Length: 86
Length: 42
Ligand SMILES: *[C@@H]1O[C@H](CO)[C@@H](O[C@@H]2O[C@H](CO)[C@@H](O)[C@H](O)[C@H]2NC(C)=O)[C@H](O)[C@H]1NC(C)=O
Ligand SMILES: *[C@@H]1O[C@H](CO)[C@@H](O)[C@H](O)[C@H]1NC(C)=O
Ligand SMILES: *[C@@H]1O[C@H](CO)[C@@H](O)[C@H](O)[C@H]1NC(C)=O
Ligand SMILES: *[C@@H]1O[C@H](CO)[C@@H](O)[C@H](O)[C@H]1NC(C)=O
View 1: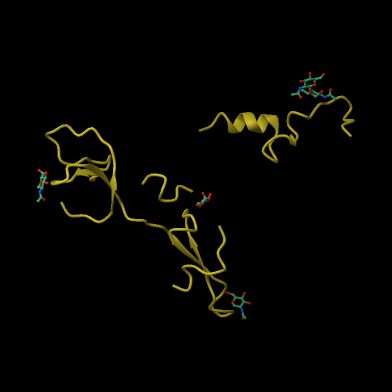
View 2: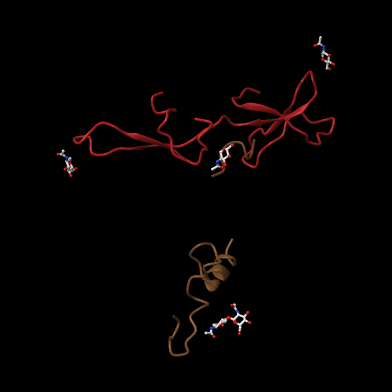
C-alpha cells in the first residue's frame, strides 16, 4: 500500500486479523507496522488554500498571499518575514 | 436615557455584558442553531 502523508503513533483496537483502517471515503486512515506492530494513523500532508490579493496589474505588481485557515506557523519571499498577520 | 414612553427595548437592544454587540434575543437565536489548522486532527 503506497501513499503520502504523516505517520503518527496512535492507539486503536486492531483485532489480530486486520492490517489497516479505512476512512468514511474508503481511504486508509491507520496502518499496523508489519514489523514493530503498532497501529499508527496516516494523516494527509499539510495542505492549504492559497489566494493572491493584488491591486490592478497596471497599478503595480506587488501582491499579498492569504493561506486559508492555517495558523501562521506551518507556512519563498511570501512564506515568512516581518510582515505577517494572523 | 430610555424614556421611550414605557416601551422596553432592553431585550432587543445591545447588552453591554454580552458578546460585544448581541442582544438577549439575538443570543437566544444564535444558541438555537448549530480555523481547524492542521494540528487539531493530527
Ligand atoms: C425592561 O425589561 C427588563 C427585563 O425584561 C427589566 O430588567 C429586569 O429588572 C428587574 C427589576 O425590576 C430585575 O429583577 C430583572 O432581573 C431584570 N431582568 C433583566 C433580564 O435584566 C428592566 O428593568 C425593564 N426596564 C424598565 C425601565 O422597567
Ligand atoms: C522482525 O519482525 C518481528 C515482528 O514479527 C520483530 O519482533 C523483530 O524484532 C524483527 N527483527 C528484525 C531484525 O527486524
Ligand atoms: C488600472 O486599471 C483600473 C481598471 O481595471 C483603474 O481603475 C485604475 O485606475 C488603473 N490604474 C492606473 C494607474 O492606470
Ligand atoms: C497558533 O498557534 C499558537 C501556538 O502558540 C497559538 O497560541 C495560537 O492561538 C494559534 N492561533 C490560532 C488562531 O489558533
